[PDB]
Amino acid sequence: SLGPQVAEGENVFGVCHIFASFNDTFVHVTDLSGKETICRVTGGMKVKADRDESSPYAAMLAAQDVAQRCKELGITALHIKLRATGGNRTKTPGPGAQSALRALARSGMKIGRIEDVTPIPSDSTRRKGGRRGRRL
RNA sequence: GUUCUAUUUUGUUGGUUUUCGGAACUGAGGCCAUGAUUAAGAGGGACGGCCGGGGGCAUUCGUAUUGCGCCGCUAGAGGUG
Ligand SMILES: [Mg+2]
Ligand SMILES: [Mg+2]
């Protein structure tokens, strides 16, 4: 729990997988390989009404909690891997993506490299919804 | 030339071949300014270099999706106004 015993001034790098859907948000800090996870907090465990799991406020609270104990385990800097639902479904990030990423910068964490890792297909299976679409 | 053959012809009876004519068949000729319009901003076909998610058969790659096996950490995740 004391982290790595390494000289001062360096930055131990981790990666946070920011998965921002339209109905909740994930903030998931792991080590460089991604094999070993460290902190995982969603907007759903920080808000009471599930209509607000994807709200930008819940993401900022979720990001603060992750970064708060991320210092505790020794990590000082992060690589950012933003992600939308993607796949066969939408490919734009949800509302909570910006607040969660902004909060990490303000929480004292150091930002490394930001990249989008949305799972886009070459071409996919048939998309949910009829031929006339989700009509309302 | 051959065959059949109208009929004229030998003072008048009779027999044969002519030729003269008619019709058909068959040789060697000479002669014609000797005889085939053009080549459709019609078409068909040939040939030459290309062109195209045209067609059929086989082959190859790509993420994504679903499922499964293992590893990590966790209490929610999904969905909706
Ligand atoms: Mg229906
Ligand atoms: Mg309408």
Image (tube, coloured by chain):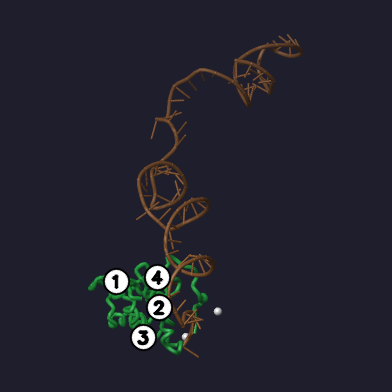
Q: Are marks 4 and 1 in contact (CB under 8 Å)?
A: no
Q: Are marks 4 and 3 in contact (CB under 8 Å)?
A: no
- Are there few (<14), some (14-19), or many (20+) residues within 10 Å of tag 3? some
Q: Which residue is mark 1?
A: A5
Amino acid residing under circle 2: Arg
Q: Nearer the viewer, mark 3 or mark 2?
A: 2
User: What colour do you see for chain A?
Assistant: green
Say whether disc 3 or disc 2 marks the residue closer to the N-terminus. 2
Residue occupying the point 45% across, 89% down: A49
Q: Secondary structure at mark 4?
A: loop
Say whether disc 2 or disc 1 marks the residue closer to the N-terminus. 1
Parent chain of label 4: A
Residue A44 - label: none
Residue A36 - label: 4
Identify the image quadrant of residue A53. bottom left
Q: Which residue is mark 3?
A: A61
Q: Which residue is mark 2?
A: A40
Q: Nearer the viewer, mark 2 or mark 4?
A: 4
Say whether disc 1 or disc 3 marks the residue closer to the N-terminus. 1
- Are there few (<14), some (14-19), or many (20+) residues within 10 Å of tag 2? some
Q: Secondary structure at mark 1?
A: loop
